[PDB]
């Protein structure tokens, strides 16, 4: 079958569970679309409830920050008339506002501004849809695909720079507050039976290094790359290339979301993470199979220095096999970050700078996560992972 008609193999990770992931492979000829701009993409997707099987080819670059005439939209185009960053900073400075959630005029005007941009950049992917890049240079720029539906395939696309002009100040986030932006490249929000394969995710021409600090905190314009929340389940992400980005992949958005227990069943394999800071992935609750991924970076780079690969969140159940981490000078323990409620990690065959290590043991965690993956393809020997992943992962690799 051609790329648009290809489906997830029956053993290929959690996405292959039950009815599996066939996306729009059954599309009639009338439901095969080629799109080269935001209007065409919106047209092809239709309503969030459009379950008609469909195939959508992305041709060239689709900039999502554009108007109905495909004209670029910048900050001033979205900015609410009443919003002003300097006034917002004065309004909510912890020295005069304290640590309560911002509210009142400036925060209302920021929220309106954010919603104006969201209306352009975020699109819902309806059920039974396959979206694939044409050739080797298909790009989605500024966009955030949201998947709340079942049975969706996304392949062979480079997603760049899902950038929020109006990050929200959250003074209770973390120990000193944080700025939080709204857009990921792909947000799986309750979505099920999803395959993300041979895509590239990066921050385009707007790396985080150029962002100022306000209240001593990075004014963060990006969020995640491929995130999963709200009972998302049965997902495979394979052969993707994540690069030059801070928070890559968060699975399970909250310690309070206990309904995520038994869900967030995700398989990550043969992905490449290069100059990714953290969350690769950060997991709460889920049974997440992580195998044959390649992580590379430097703790001392001026842009996107490595912090950790796996985030052991509340009740997480990561089962890791044959993954390879090249971060010169890193200790075995620092390959992961352990959060409260994070007590267990299975890892086998982990290599760090060529040395066999045991990340779980190095952090004194339980060696068992209470399950063993059964749905998976062939697991490469660790010694072959770097080469296989560098050569095969990312958009533009299928010709
Ligand atoms: O639970 C989380 O995932 C956590 O993530 C962000 O925080 C991270 C990190 O988890 C924090 O411990 C903190 O890390 C600091 C440096 O960034 C890190 O390199 C190291 O030096 O430790 C520092 C520290 O202990 O303070 O901040 C990180 C960051 O700012 O990205 C969220 O900010 C946080 O709210 C929470 O979600
Ligand atoms: Ca997100």
Image (tube, helix red, strand yellow):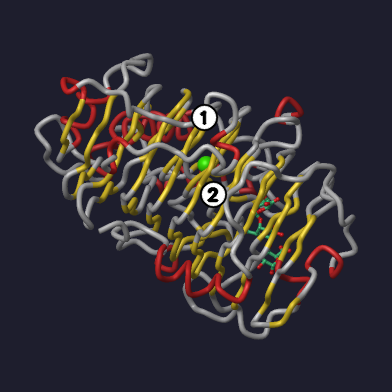
Residue 357 rendering spot, x and y as whole percentages: 77, 75
How far apart, in angstroms, are the residues tagged by discs 2 and 1? 38 Å
- In the figure, 85 relative to 253: above or below? below
Which quadrant of the figure contains the C terminus?
A: bottom left
Q: Residue furthest bottom?
A: 329
- In the figure, 80 relative to 295: above or below? above
Residue 246 rendering spot, x and y as whole percentages: 52, 60
Quarter holding ligand 1: bottom right
Does residue 233 appear left or right of residue 243 in this picture? right
Q: Nearer the viewer, mark 2 or mark 1?
A: 1
Q: Residue furthest left?
A: 69
Q: Earlier in the sequence, mark 2 or mark 1?
A: 1
**Depth check: 256 or 104 in front?**
256
Identify the residue at image location x=62%, y=57%.
Answer: 291
On residue 179, which mark appears?
Answer: 2
Mark 1 lies on residue: 20
Please tell me whether mark 2 sits on a helix, a strand or a loop. Answer: strand
Which quadrant of the figure contains the N terminus?
A: top left
Q: Residues within 10 Å of mark 2 (few under 14, many from 20)?
A: many
């Amino acid at each position: 079958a051609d790329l648009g008609h290809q489906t997830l193999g029956s053993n290929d990770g959690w996405g292959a569970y039950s009815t599996g992931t066939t996306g729009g492979s059954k599309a009639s000829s009338s439901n095969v679309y080629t799109v080269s701009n935001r209007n065409q993409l919106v047209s092809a997707l239709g309503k969030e409830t459009n379950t008609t099987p469909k195939i959508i080819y992305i041709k060239g670059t689709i900039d999502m920050n554009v108007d109905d005439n495909l004209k670029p939209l910048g900050l001033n185009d979205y900015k609410d008339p009443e919003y002003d960053l300097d006034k917002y900073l004065k309004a909510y400075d912890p020295s005069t506002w304290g640590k309560k959630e911002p509210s009142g005029t400036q925060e209302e005007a920021r929220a309106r501004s954010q919603k104006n941009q969201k209306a352009r950049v975020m699109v819902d992917i309806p059920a039974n849809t396959t979206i694939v890049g044409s050739g080797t240079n298909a790009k989605v720029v500024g966009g955030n695909f949201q998947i709340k539906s079942d049975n969706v395939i996304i392949r062979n696309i480079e997603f760049q720079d899902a950038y929020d002009y109006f990050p929200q100040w959250d003074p209770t986030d973390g120990s000193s507050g944080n700025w939080n932006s709204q857009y990921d490249n792909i947000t799986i929000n309750g979505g099920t039976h999803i395959w993300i394969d041979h895509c590239t995710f990066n921050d385009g021409s707007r790396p985080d290094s150029t962002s100022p600090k306000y209240y001593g905190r990075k004014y963060q314009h990006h969020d995640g790359q491929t995130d999963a929340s709200n009972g998302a389940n049965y997902i495979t992400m394979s052969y993707n290339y994540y690069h030059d980005h801070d928070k890559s992949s968060i699975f399970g958005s909250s310690d309070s979301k206990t309904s995520d227990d038994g869900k967030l069943k995700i398989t990550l394999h043969h992905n490449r993470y290069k100059n990714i800071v953290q969350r690769a992935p950060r997991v709460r609750f889920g049974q997440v199979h992580v195998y044959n991924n390649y992580y590379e970076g430097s703790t001392s780079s001026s842009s996107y220095p490595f912090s950790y690969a796996w985030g052991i969140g509340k009740s997480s159940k990561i089962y890791a096999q044959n993954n390879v981490i090249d971060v010169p000078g890193l200790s075995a323990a620092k390959t992961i970050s352990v959060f409260s409620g994070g007590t267990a990690l299975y890892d086998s065959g982990t290599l760090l700078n060529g040395t066999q290590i045991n990340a779980s043991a190095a952090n004194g965690l339980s060696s068992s996560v209470g399950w063993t993956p059964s749905l998976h393809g062939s697991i490469d020997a660790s010694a072959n992972v770097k080469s296989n992943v560098i050569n095969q992962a990312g958009a533009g690799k299928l010709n």
